[PDB]
Amino acid sequence: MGSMERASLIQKAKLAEQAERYEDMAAFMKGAVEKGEELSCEERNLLSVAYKNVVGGQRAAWRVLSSIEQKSNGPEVREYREKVETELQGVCDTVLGLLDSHLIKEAGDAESRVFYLKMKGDYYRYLAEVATGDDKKRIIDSARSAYQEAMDISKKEMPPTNPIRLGLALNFSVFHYEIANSPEEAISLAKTTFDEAMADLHTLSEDSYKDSTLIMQLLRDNLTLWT
Amino acid sequence: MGSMERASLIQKAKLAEQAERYEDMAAFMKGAVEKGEELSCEERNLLSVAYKNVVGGQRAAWRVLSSIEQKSNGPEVREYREKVETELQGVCDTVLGLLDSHLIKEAGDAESRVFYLKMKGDYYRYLAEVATGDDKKRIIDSARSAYQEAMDISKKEMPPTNPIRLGLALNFSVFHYEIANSPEEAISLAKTTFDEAMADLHTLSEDSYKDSTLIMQLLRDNLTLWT
Amino acid sequence: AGSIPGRR
Amino acid sequence: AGSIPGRR
Ligand SMILES: *Cc1ccc(C(=O)NCc2cccc(OC)c2)cc1
Ligand SMILES: *Cc1ccc(C(=O)NCc2cccc(OC)c2)cc1
Ligand SMILES: [Cl-]
Ligand SMILES: [Cl-]
Ligand SMILES: [Cl-]
Ligand SMILES: [Cl-]
Ligand SMILES: [Mg+2]
Ligand SMILES: [Mg+2]
C-alpha cells in the first residue's frame, strides 16, 4: 500500500468495515501504520477491529478442524489444520510486527500505550492457543508480560471505569483462565475489576456510563460461567 | 493444487465447508476439477456451494459499496468499489472457465448438464449485476442462453419436482425479474413451475417431498414479493 | 427476490 | 469465556 495516501487508506479501511471485508480492512490499516505516523484513537480502533475479525475467523476455523482432528485420533485433516494454523500464526506475527515496528515505542500517552500492549498480549494469547512445542511456555510468558505492563500503566493512569482498562482486565482474565491454567487468578481479577468500576460509575456521564457498564456485563458473564 | 491427490482435494473441500472457509473450499474444488475427471453429484454440489459462497460475499460487499457510491454522487469509494468489482468478475470468470474447460462438454446426463448450465447462467447473471458498458447486453444474452438450454433439457428429461429443475427455474425467474426487466415473464415462470411441481408431489417419497416443497416455498416467497 | 441456496 | 469485542 506504499503508493496510497494515508488518508485514503484510512477512508478505505472504514469502507471495508462497512462492507464486512475485514481482510481488506487489515491490509489498509497495515498500510496506514507503515506510513510511520502515530495513530489516533479512532485509527487504533480501526487497526484492532480489522485484525481481531481476521484472526477471529481463523481461530474459529482452527477450532473446528482441531476438533475433527481429535475425533479422528489419512493425513488430510492434520494437513489442513496445519495450513490454517500457519496462516493464523502469520497474521499474529504481522500484528506483533506492527506493534514492535514501531507503534509501541512511539506510544507515550496511557490510552495509546495500554491499547497497544493489550493487543500485544492478545496476539501472543492467540499464538499460545495453538502452541504445543518448545516455545509454548515462552509464548505464554510473552503474553503475560505484555498484559502485565499494560495493567501496571492502566492502574496508575486510568480511572477504573475506563473502557480500555476494563477490556484489558477482561482479556487478561481470559488469559489467566484459558491459557495460564489459573482460574482463581482469573476470577479474582474479574471480580476486583468489576467492583472497582462499580464504585466509580457515579463519576460518569450517561454515555460513559453506558460504555463502562457494557464491558462490566462481560466481566459478570465470565464470572457467572466460572463460578 | 496440481500436486495434491484428487481425493484429498475433495476431502479438504468438505473440511473447509465445515470450517466455513469458502475461499479454501473453492480453491480445493478448482483443483479437483482441473484433475480432468468428471464430477459426481456430491462433487458438483461442493463446487457450486464453494463458489456461491465466495461470490455471495463479494456481491454483498459490492452492493454496500455501490450504495455508498451512489449516495456520494474523493475517488476512494469508486476506487474501492472497482477493486471489489474486479475481484468478483475474476471469480465469475474462473467458474465460467471451469465450466467451459471442460465440465459442460463432458456432461452427458441430464442431472450434470442441467446443473452446469444453471451455474453458467448464474455466473453470467452475477457478471450482469455489475455490468454497465459495451458488453452488458452480451453478458445478459449469455446468461439467458445458458438458462434457456438448461430449461429445455430439464423439461425434456426431468420430472417437474426435480430439485435441480426447480432451482433452475427459480434462478431463471430471478434473472427475468432482476436482470432482464421482464417481471411478467418472471412471475409466469415461477407460477407455472410451482403449479406443475404441486401436481407431481403425489409421486414422491417423504424425503423427496421435503426436498421439492422446500424449493417450491422459495418460488412462492418470490411470487408473494412480486405480486 | 431469493435465488437458490446451495445447502438445506 | 468471552474476550472483548471491537465495536458496540
Ligand atoms: C441448482 C440447485 C442447487 C441447490 C438445490 C437445493 O436443493 N438446495 C437446498 C435448498 C433448497 C431450498 C431452500 C434452501 O434453504 C436452506 C435450501 C437445488 C437446485
Ligand atoms: C481493548 C478494548 C477494545 C474495545 C473496547 C470497547 O469498548 N468495545 C465495545 C464493546 C464492549 C463490550 C461489549 C460489546 O459488545 C457489542 C462491545 C474496550 C477495550
Ligand atoms: Cl492443506
Ligand atoms: Cl508519541
Ligand atoms: Cl482500492
Ligand atoms: Cl460424460
Ligand atoms: Mg502523503
Ligand atoms: Mg492421483
Image (cartoon, coloured by chain):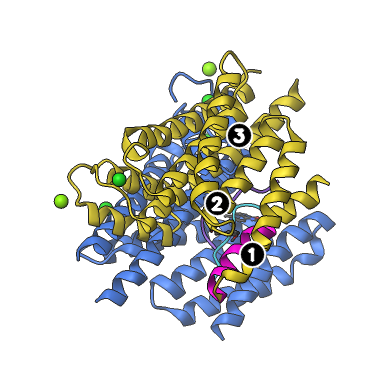
Chain colours: A blue, B yellow, C purple, D cyan
Give how far across and how far down residue A30 sits, in percent. 46, 35
Q: Is residue A56 above or below residue A96?
A: below
Secondary element under disc 1, as helix, strand or loop, is helix
Q: Is residue B203 left or right of residue A1?
A: right
Is B208 magenta? The answer is yes
For the stretch drawn in magenta, the main secondary structure is helix
Residue type at tag 1? Thr
Query: Who comes first in sequence, dot 2 or dot 1?
Result: 2
Please tell me the numbered disc located at residue B165.
2
Nearest the eye: A177 or B109: B109
Label 3: which residue?
Answer: B62
Q: Is residue A72 left or right of residue D3?
A: left
* Magenta extent: B206-217
Q: Is residue A203 above or below residue B60?
A: below
Measured in 3D between alpha carbons, the distance from the residue under mark 2 to the one under mark 1, in whole angstroms, is 13 Å
Label 1: which residue?
Answer: B213
